[PDB]
Amino acid sequence: NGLIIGIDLGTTNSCVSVMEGGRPVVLENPEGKRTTPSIVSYKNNEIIVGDAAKRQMVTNPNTIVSIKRLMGTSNKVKVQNADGTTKELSPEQVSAQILSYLKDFAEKKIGKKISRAVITVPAYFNDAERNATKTAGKIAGLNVERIINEPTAAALAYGIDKASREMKVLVYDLGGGTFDVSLLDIAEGTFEVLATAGDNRLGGDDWDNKIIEYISAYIAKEHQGLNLSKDKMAMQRLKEAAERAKIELSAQLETIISLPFLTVTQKGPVNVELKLTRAKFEELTKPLLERTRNPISDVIKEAKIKPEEINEILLVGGSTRMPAVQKLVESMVPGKKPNRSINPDEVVAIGAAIQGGVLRGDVKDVLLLDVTPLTLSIETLGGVATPLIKRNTTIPVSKSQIFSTAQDNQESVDVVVCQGERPMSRDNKSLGRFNLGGIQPAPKGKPQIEITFSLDANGILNVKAKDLTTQKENSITISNLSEEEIQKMIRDAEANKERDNIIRERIELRNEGELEHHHH
Ligand SMILES: Nc1ncnc2c1ncn2[C@@H]1O[C@H](COP(=O)(O)OP(=O)(O)O)[C@@H](O)[C@H]1O
């Protein structure tokens, strides 16, 4: 029946995506962000999810971070209610609050109720870990139609199921909390995780902490051993400044960590304005980064292949935007360029969304092709399809030819557009019709009407009929196609090729084409 949304339920951030008109689309939360902190907080008997919970993660003791780590387990998390009593919550319930939130704002964006989803998980996850994830989904009112692996999701986003050949794919996932490297074998639509290895206590958070150590060391140096470890408001601000600094060093060779009024001492207010170079940040985080090297070789050997045999490498996780990470990965797979062309923090959700569409039935797969798959033609005298843009021409393009009138004293012309490789326009699929009058009584062949088929680089078509004498010009704009639908029309022409050529004997396109008027 209804839409099946794609959810990446991540350790540190979550992302939600859905198929819209044959494309995956990432949905943005109410704060306009395409990803959402996997963080829940409790205050005044009100549940807070995402950015607002992250903004009080150190200050509010109730905040629950990295709940995903306790999934599958029987552990509990205790939080204070308003009255001082203690409520106890399972990892299924906390995750269900995050999923409810994602589900909520998606309904508001889509404007429909949503009750089905694909949820992704780490490849290593066992059945309890997956049943807790599935139970989270049920508590949130979502029929979980399938649970898929994060790196399998990544491969669907990159259309690797469409390769029509065996593919060895290395997926390097460095998130905020977790690192995973997986080796996939993808053959005839079956996804097999040959091998997985990594560290679920290693991620971009650990990179930030080295910046917190840096800022701390600097403060102690500058202010006679000033230590703010036990100050919650201070530590909240450092954690945030650390992550801002880190992110800026993925596009800058340095940055300024700026923390005015960090605290006040008997000396007055302490202001930090601290430079951190990319070189320095890389040095401080070298130990963390290098814990990702051996795992790459480990899974390569575990699946009994050379590096040579790897067909494609995908970068997943937002921490893979870091230059040092991209460089590392490249160093371990000579020849291959790691693929980062789909937002690594969105890529998994996108894959789930694709899987969702495929499970539904509405797999109206649009294709952003740079070349025209079929001939585009105007109907001339006798129902003949005179081509203007030939099959396999590269967009953008605008071809033009002058036509005339089929009958003497003809007041107007019908501009009937059609797509396909067949000699009669009735055989081809029509894309539109429109009229153009203003035409003065004359012999057939006298009026000179410049027709212009025009395609933008995004694909869509505009056909511009112009009477050159009277300047009168009507024009229509056109919608796109499926792969099966393309192939049906190619097949149809292939199937009637003998019939069509005998029709073509009588057709002569080298003379000026003629457009007629049949009454609407
Ligand atoms: N431009 C960037 N440079 C460095 N790190 C980044 C950048 N953008 C996002 N990150 C980091 O990505 C990490 C995790 O992102 P994400 O993939 O959403 O995590 P997860 O999949 O674990 O939920 C965060 O620690 C964040 O600091």
Image (cartoon, rainbow, N blue to C red):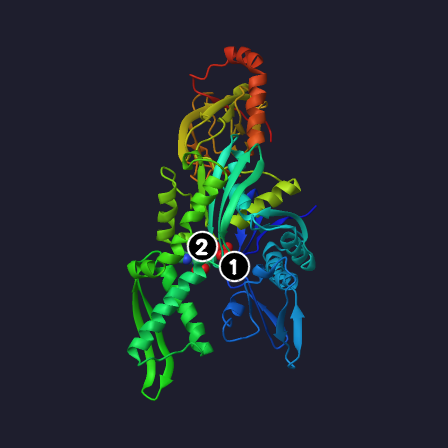
* Residue 103 falls left or right of residue 247: right
Report the disc number at residue 160: none
If the image is split into quadrants, where does the C terminus sit?
top right
Name the quarter showing ligand 1.
bottom left
Q: Earlier in the sequence, mark 1 or mark 2?
A: 1
Residue under the image location 62 percent in, 55 percent down? 111
Q: Is residue 371 above or below residue 289?
A: above
CB atoms at circles 1 and 2 under 8 Å apart?
A: yes
Q: Is residue 453 among the parts visible in the rendering?
A: yes
If the image is split into quadrants, where does the N terminus sit?
top right
SS of the residue at dot 1?
strand
SS of the residue at dot 2?
helix
Question: Which of the two residues, 384 or 446, is positioned nearer the viewer here?
Answer: 384
The residue that disc 1 covers is: 13
Report the disc number at residue 318: 2
Residue 267 placement: quadrant = bottom left
> Is the CB atom of the residue marked by disc 1 within 8 angstroms of ligand 1's nearest atom?
yes
Question: Which of the two residues, 143 or 428, is positioned nearer the viewer here?
Answer: 143
Image location of residue 48, percent across then percent down: 58, 69
Image location of residue 136, percent across then percent down: 65, 58
Neighbour tally class for label 2: few under 14, some 14-19, many 20 plus, Cα within 10 Å? some
Image location of residue 155, percent across then percent down: 52, 42
Q: Is residue 460 among the parts visible in the rendering?
A: no
Query: Which three-letter amino acid code belongs to the residue tagged 1?
Result: Asn
Image location of residue 200, percent across then percent down: 51, 56
> Is the CB atom of the residue marked by disc 2 within 8 angstroms of ligand 1's nearest atom?
yes
